[PDB]
Image: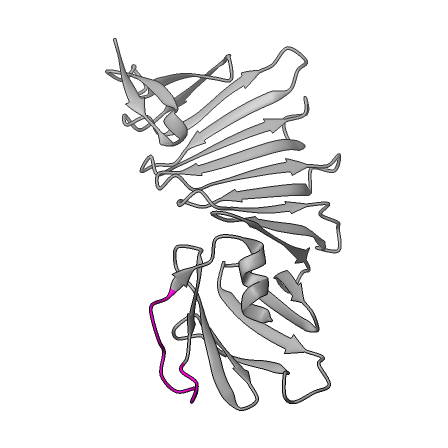
Amino acid sequence: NSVSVDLPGSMKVLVSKSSNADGKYDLIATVDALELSGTSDKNNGSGVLEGVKADASKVKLTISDDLGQTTLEVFKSDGSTLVSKFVTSKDKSSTFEKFNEKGEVSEKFITRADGTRLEYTGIKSDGSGKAKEVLKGYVLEGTLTAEKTTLVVKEGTVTLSKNISKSGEVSVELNDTDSSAATKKTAAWNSGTSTLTITVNSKKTKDLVFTSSNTITVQQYDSNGTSLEGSAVEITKLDEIKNALK
């Protein structure tokens, strides 16, 4: 009769085993206790399913042609003003967006494949908002502008800024307002190694590596400031970032 097809986000869609006189396949799924239905000219479980809630809100599930992504939209009763959208990928990454009354994004929660999160709240029409990055062991706080996301850690007169572009590219900078050259921190970012090298009084002191696993490691230099010693150690809490900035 039907074939159950496994989709991202542990969702399932039933597809008819064979096509009708028009060559089309029937699709059925149950999402959040609502039965959705649709038809497709493909036999693999891809296509669009729709349902209508008790309250007249319209639900639409779109399964991409290669089954790599699901988009689950809830609309107002007009079928066009978004209330929410979940987009889930095969790799386990996802996005959840909430919309305001004009159907424009007001909150956006990104879950990466590794389970870390980037959370945008209080999003305004000017593109600004509040940002929080949820990592293994700790969270970073900052802001969103149209230009970029900037997460900030302050320690004494030092400010560490972790910038994330719209496409997820990380760059990091440091500024210290310390008026003494004996203690003022400066830093160089190397985009090629995702590493921030801190210097104090003309001696390199530490490398902070911002890894592809969304972690930070720290490693110290020798007293002459030209050779790394020991091994890189993973930072496990915000206070350990602050320690590296002292």
The dominant secondary structure in magenta is: loop
Q: Can residue 163 be seen from the camera position used here?
A: no
Against 170, is 142 above or below? above
Counting from the top left corner in percent of width and height, residue 215 is at 44, 56
Counting from the top left corner in percent of width and height, residue 176 is at 67, 78
Q: Quadrant of residue 91?
A: top left
Image position of 151 (left or right of 157): left
Residue appearing at x 49%, y 88% in the figure = 203
Residue appearing at x 50%, y 21% in the figure = 50
Q: Where are the magenta residues, as a range?
A: 222-232
| Quadrant in which the N terminus appears | top left
| Quadrant in which the C terminus appears | bottom right
Against 211, is 182 above or below? below
The number of numbered badges drawn on the structure is 0
Residue appearing at x 59%, y 63% in the figure = 242
Counting from the top left corner in percent of width and height, residue 40 is at 36, 25
Q: Using the image as rendered, state which of residue 66 and residue 176 is in the foreground.
A: 176
Residue appearing at x 57%, y 89% in the figure = 201
Counting from the top left corner in percent of width and height, residue 197 is at 48, 78
Residue 143 is covered by the magenta coloring: no
